[PDB]
Each structure stands twice: as structure tokens, then as C-alpha cells.
Image (cartoon, coloured by chain):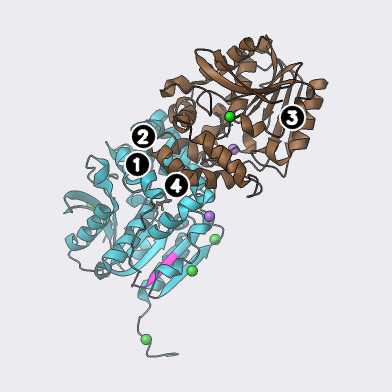
Chain colours: A cyan, B brown
Amino acid sequence: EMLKHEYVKVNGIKMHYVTQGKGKLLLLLHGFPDFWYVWRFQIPALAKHFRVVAPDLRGYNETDKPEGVENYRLDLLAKDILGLIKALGEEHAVVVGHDWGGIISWTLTAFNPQAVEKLVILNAPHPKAYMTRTKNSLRQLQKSWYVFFFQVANIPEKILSRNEFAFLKNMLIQSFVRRDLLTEEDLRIYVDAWSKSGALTSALNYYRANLNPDIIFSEKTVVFPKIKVPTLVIWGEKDVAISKDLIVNMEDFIEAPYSIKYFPECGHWVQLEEPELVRKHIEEFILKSDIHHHHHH
Amino acid sequence: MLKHEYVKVNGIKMHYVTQGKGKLLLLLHGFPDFWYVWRFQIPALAKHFRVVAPDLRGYNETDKPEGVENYRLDLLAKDILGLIKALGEEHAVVVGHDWGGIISWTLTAFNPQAVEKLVILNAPHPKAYMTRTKNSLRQLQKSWYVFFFQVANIPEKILSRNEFAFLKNMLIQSFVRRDLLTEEDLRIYVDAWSKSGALTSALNYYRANLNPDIIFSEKTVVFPKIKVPTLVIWGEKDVAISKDLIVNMEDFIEAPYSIKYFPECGHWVQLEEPELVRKHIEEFILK
Ligand SMILES: C=C(C)[C@@H]1CC[C@](C)(O)[C@@H](Cl)C1
Ligand SMILES: C=C(C)[C@@H]1CC[C@](C)(O)[C@@H](Cl)C1
Ligand SMILES: C=C(C)[C@@H]1CC[C@](C)(O)[C@@H](Cl)C1
Ligand SMILES: C=C(C)[C@@H]1CC[C@](C)(O)[C@@H](Cl)C1
Ligand SMILES: [Cl-]
Ligand SMILES: [Cl-]
Ligand SMILES: [Cl-]
Ligand SMILES: [Cl-]
Ligand SMILES: [Cl-]
Ligand code: NA
Ligand code: NA
């Protein structure tokens, strides 16, 4: 059965996703400035075993793009995924998230553990670690320069988009470990998703709603339940956007089986750089029995 | 005796301190400093020169016009041009750190008749900044706070609350040694930061001159070549400025140029190697 495109109403918006395979629901959630297509190396391999669903998140590509910054608050983003699980006819999913998708995945898992059977994170800090540590970390504040850039209304969208997205392409390419990670053909495909009307504003609204300076430098402390479901973290260490300072003691946030696979020579997009090892680690993690009553048989 | 003075320039009243007689030597501070950043150099240089260290527009005891467009670089440069004239002079030796240095590059480029010699501490040439930053991940990262400062009200609140806790902390994290300022120094700094209007005026420099439309412009900035002898002093461990912005200055200067690197110093080289900085300045002027 091939890859198919589908559209479903969730949490008041119409969400586009692609799906391939049958079996356990395995959600793959992209981040900025990607869309479902970031998972193109994992979808067919994982679809050999699982029902893979890769949505475009609120605001992105073919998904609806509500107006207004407060329509991009993280609680709504997580509810979109909760609603997607239900709309797919399911009650539980294995949830894999990269970048913003990882932020949403940590959140959904912490606040809605009933919906998440197992959690996989690629290169997204735990939200509490980001909120606690960034204000005190010059290294992270530097790496988060673009978060502050994106807070200004109107102007960042125009800058990123001018000259057929020259700055967005350049800023994206400079975030990679090797400059040639995406082909020109990949870049054409990305420009098509970036050009959907309203998409770029909606994507930057995630930073305006959730990472504005009042939040970053808040004196309030964020209450975040411990993660209570098995968790796999895949981490490219050469990540331009996230300091290793933010993943120190990351296992403290987890009260369940936890494994981390470090990729010392990979950056923020390990799924594009070591696709086969990513696929393998995810599959082994999902298929591992949680009950071990036949050692060495 | 170090003396405080006020003088009208370019429609504003400017405060400055002065000591000594002879050749006019201007020392121009940047953010988040004021004349007092020059405390180690003023007495030594005053032995041979007429040292004047002003508070720039918006800072400490100088006037603080309201409105972002009152902080455009051309107005800041005209303030210094006006100061030279108000001091009874037609030219000065001009030493600038940080924003002081940006203004000094600008004054020197557009008004060479007003500048005998130019000294820059840790300030990139403006055209180098404008050309390079938009394409430099390293510089964009170091420039995070430039973008933070674009937002109205919130940066002032964050920097100032709890008696400037964040500004002190971020300032201290920018030093080579965490003990560079004494408690006494910090009290003096807080007093200047707390002048009515001072913090908003200082951040207005970034809003007027370093907003994203300027940084990411593809227009070329027209900037005459520097035509007077120039010494650049550069602390290499600068948290705010990539070394990528000071290399390869040949396009920008058509006069004698020398650069002195301080490998073990950061942005505040005049505080970290006070004696060597003073020595290089003196030797350069007296040659
Ligand atoms: C929302 C966040 C705390 C994070 C910040 C860092 C990145 C890289 O922009 C992505 Cl993971 C989103
Ligand atoms: C457009 C940008 C400034 C980049 C794009 C890639 C990331 C991972 O989202 C962060 Cl580094 C921001
Ligand atoms: C181009 C500018 C206006 C510069 C940029 C770097 C600094 C450190 O913030 C000061 Cl030197 C101002
Ligand atoms: C207040 C800040 C966030 C910092 C500290 C002072 C500097 C050197 O001007 C740059 Cl690092 C901005
Ligand atoms: Cl289809
Ligand atoms: Cl850990
Ligand atoms: Cl690796
Ligand atoms: Cl068991
Ligand atoms: Cl004073
Ligand atoms: Na840190
Ligand atoms: Na660079």
C-alpha cells in the first residue's frame, strides 16, 4: 500500500498528514522550518512494521493556519496531536518529535500520558530545561538569537521570504553540519511548503506565543509532570541551536525506562544524516518487549 | 584635577569630564558604560593631553531626547563634531570603544578634517558589520541581544528589575575575570543606569541603527575610506564581536593602519590591560 495524503478535523482545525503502513500508530512530528517531508527517509522503512502518520503541524504546509499569535500556544499544539490520535481511530500512539515536534511530544507525554505509549525525541530540549537554563546561559542565549529575531511583528517574515526565500534558505543551510545536506531539489520542495499563504507567519507565531522574552526571563517556575512512559532520545551533538548545557541531567525529567543515543558527528537533523541508524534505534525501541520472562531463550 | 562640565552641542546638553592641557583627546564610551569606563586612562593621558570623556546622547548626565529616531548614528556623530567645536577646537584625537568606536569610525570617515588620529577599541567598522553580519552565523549568535533589544518596553523591564540584576549578570559574564568590577564600581554603574530615561535611550541606539531591516539590507552602505592614521586595539575574547568582523580592513582604510591584538582580553580591553592600552594610545599619538 503506498503513501497516502489525508486531511482530518482536529481541535477546530483541518490538519494534513501523510500515512503509510499498518499496525501500531507511530506519529512523526516535524519542527521549524520543515513539514512532513523531513521524515521522507524514515516513513517507508518504518511503514514496514507500523502505521506511520506524519502530519503538518498547525500553521504549516497544507494544514490550517489560524490568525493570531495566541492560536499557537503550546497547549493548543498539543491538543491538536491528542485530537489527531482520536481522529485516526486510535487511543494511543508512539510519538516521535524533532525540534518543535519534540517540544510538543515532551508536552503531550507529560500532560496526557494516557495517549502516549512510548516517546522518542530527536534534538529538542525538554521544555523545563530550556525555560530554567536559557536565561542563565550565554551560550544558549547566543544560539537562540533567532528566537529574539522572530519576536518582531511582520519584518522577520519579509526578510526570510525576500529574493525567493534567500535568507531562510541561507539561515537553514548554515544550521547544518554539511552545507549540502539538502539538494537544490529538496530546497524547491521546501520553498513550495514555505510559500503556502500565511505559512511563515504561522510558523514564527510558535516563537511569539511560547518563547517571548517575558516567558524566557520569567520568574515564575514551570510545573511539568515527570515523564512516565518509556523514552528514547536521539541527539546529534553538533546542534547549532541547542547547547549541550540544556541536556545535562536530562534523565531527571523521566521516571520510566530511558535511553539516549548520541551522534557525535551529526547536528540538529540526525534523521537526515544517519537515517538508517535512526530508523533502527526507533524500531528496536518500539518492538522491545516490556516484559522479560525468557532470558537467553 | 578632573573637572565636570556641561556644554550645548547639536541641540542637546552634553556632560563630560576633562583633565589636562594640550592636544584635545576625546575618549568615547559605549554600552552599557559612560565616561567612567575610562577611569584608568584619564589621569595618565591627562599628563600630556587635554582629555575629554563625554557621556554620549542618552547616557548618564547627558540629555536624553525621546524617540528612537533621535538615536540615528548621523545624529550621534554630529554630537561629537559639535562637541569638538564647542570645546574651542577644530580637530581632536578621537578614541572610541564599542558604540563610541562606531561613532568614531563614522566621524572620521565623513569628517577627516576633524580627526587628527583615530583609535578604535573593540568596535567593528560599520561597513564591515553591515556587509558581513547577515551572512555570519557566529556574529548573528553573538548579536542575540541586538534582536532582544528591538522589542519595546520588555527589555528595559528585564534588564532593570531587581536593581539591574540581569544587566549586571550579563555584563559580568562578558568579562575575562568575574571580579573585574568591585562592588563600588557596580554601585557607580547602577547610579548611571538609573538616570531617568537612560536605559531606554541606550537601547534606542540598537533600535535606530541595528534593526533587522538595516542588518539584512542588501543595499550597499556608502562609507568613505578612512584617511587619517588609525590604531585598532582588539581584545580577542570578545563575547559580542566575532573576529570575523575585524579581519581584512584594507578596503576601508587608505592611511597608516595598525592593529594590536590582546589575545587574553575580552570586550573591555581598557579595563583588563589598562596600562598597555594607555601605552599603545600614547605612543601612537606621540609618533
Ligand atoms: C521551543 C523551544 C524551547 C525550542 C527551542 C530550540 C529550537 C531548536 O528552536 C526548537 Cl527545538 C524549539
Ligand atoms: C531560520 C533559522 C534562523 C534556523 C532554521 C533551523 C532551526 C533549527 O529551526 C533554527 Cl537553527 C532556526
Ligand atoms: C555595528 C555596531 C553598531 C556595533 C555592533 C557590536 C556592538 C558590540 O554591540 C557595538 Cl560595538 C555596536
Ligand atoms: C546587556 C547585555 C545582554 C550585554 C552586556 C553588555 C554588552 C557588551 O554591551 C553586550 Cl554583551 C550586551
Ligand atoms: Cl494520496
Ligand atoms: Cl542524564
Ligand atoms: Cl555520529
Ligand atoms: Cl520484566
Ligand atoms: Cl558623573
Ligand atoms: Na550554559
Ligand atoms: Na563569520
Disc 4 with disc 2 on a shared chain = no
Q: Nearer the viewer, mark 3 or mark 1?
A: 3
Q: Residue B103, percent across and down? A: 59, 22
Residue extent of the magenta highlight: A227-233
Q: Secondary structure at mark 3?
A: helix
Verify whether residue B267 appears in magenta.
Answer: no
Q: Which quarter of the figure is the N terminus of chain B placed in?
A: top right
Q: Nearer the viewer, residue B176 or A177?
A: B176
Q: Are marks 4 and 2 in contact (CB under 8 Å)?
A: no
Q: Check the image and report above or below for B214 versus B91.
A: below
**Element under label 1?**
helix
Residue A256 pos. (x, y %): 38, 75
Q: Is mark 3 within 8 Å of ligand 9?
A: no
Q: Is residue B56 left or right of residue A191?
A: right
Relative to A6, A152 lies left or right = right
> Which chain letter matches label 3?
B
The residue pinned by badge 4 equals B162
- Are the two marked residues, 2 and 1, in contact with CB atoms closer than 8 angstroms? yes
- Residue A253 is at least partly visible in this image: yes
Please determine if labels 2 and 1 lie on a single subunit: yes
Task: Measuring from the top left, give residue A30's x and y in whole percent.
Answer: 35, 53
Task: State the separation of the CA atoms marked 4 and 1.
Answer: 31 Å
- From where the camera sits, is residue B123 visible? no
Q: Chain of mark 4?
A: B
Q: Is residue B53 above or below residue A149?
A: above
Q: Which residue is mark 2?
A: A157
Question: What type is the residue that disc 1 sits on?
Answer: Leu
Real-space CA distance between mark 4 and mark 2, rounded to the nearest whole angstrom: 35 Å
